[PDB]
Figure 1 (cartoon, rainbow over the protein chains, first blue to last red):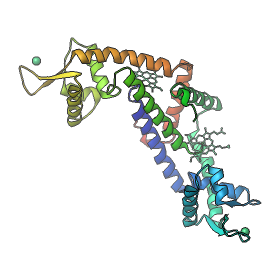
Figure 2 (cartoon, rainbow over the protein chains, first blue to last red; figure 1 turned 90 degrees about the vertical axis):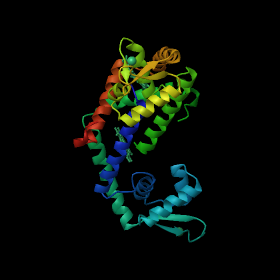
Figure 3 (cartoon, chains in turn purple, yellow; figure 1 turned 135 degrees about the horizontal axis):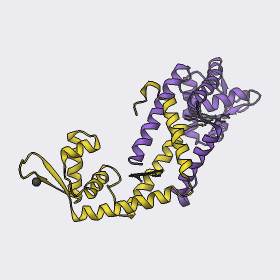
Figure 4 (tube, chains in turn orange, cyan; figure 1 turned 45 degrees about the vertical axis):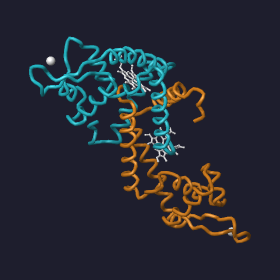
Length: 147
Length: 147
Ligand code: HEM
Ligand code: HEM
Ligand SMILES: [Co+2]
Ligand SMILES: [Co+2]
């Protein structure tokens, strides 16, 4: 269709605006991306621990990025960063009272968000749409289908 | 799905790259957007004429933009800009030999492009996909469904 790139970008920009507004309403700002992922990981596996190294592996990111991410999670009060008692070179992450509230709020938000967004759309229609995208991606990438 | 905005943007960026590479191969660079639209309009209605004012109305753009667009079409050698003989305040646009070659090349390109992109996708699947997008747009816009 005419002006393919402008129309697609106008839609994603709209969606970004929607998600940002919805997130603020549920007080789960900054949890839409990587912060959310790690908070929900901590919350759902309290048996286990997560070092900064574990964070890198879990999100497939470099040390420097992982380090920036966890420092900002701490800034936000979601986690405390405490070196290993046995070896003070390993940094372990622990969800705070606030990070735990944020976790239970984020789960609700994602449920309500999907209910709202996906109202009037079937599992079959999703499957169809997903296939058309995948086929489009495959037709216009060729040997570069490593994505 | 996780990282919704990053995944959508990575796909549109890919598509932009594809279209740019495909356009260069068919020598119809700069015709992907507004230039194409006006060249194909000129080519398909040689009976009629197109002023800069007609260009504004046809593309729903302001005078200043229309003026920048046609000056760049002239720079590219697709058109000649010649004031009305009767009234030298009306500017009329005329497709050149080159603009006409470009027009017949652009038509081929769009046919091949769609054949390639839409291979392995049915009219029903398009209709489905279109409905899911429209419903998504409607669910996440509400009163701002003026798009
Ligand atoms: C500059 C790029 C493009 C232009 C100018 C363009 C233009 C058009 C035009 C004019 C039509 C209508 C043709 C007709 O009247 O029969 C059309 C149809 C269509 N385009 Fe595009 N298009 C472009 C890129 C794309 C892309 C990237 C996609 C999808 C990846 C796409 C998907 C379609 C589809 C599905 C149709 C419907 C064809 C039909 O069944 O009639 N187009 N496009
Ligand atoms: C930050 C934003 C979002 C996050 C973190 C996110 C995350 C997720 C997650 C984790 C799932 C899997 C849930 C499960 O295991 O049951 C999921 C499913 C899904 N998401 Fe999202 N999502 C987001 C936004 C969106 C958006 C914007 C759309 C579409 C507009 C969307 C469409 C879907 C769909 C269709 C499913 C499939 C649900 C199913 O049938 O199991 N999501 N999302
Ligand atoms: Co310890
Ligand atoms: Co004249």
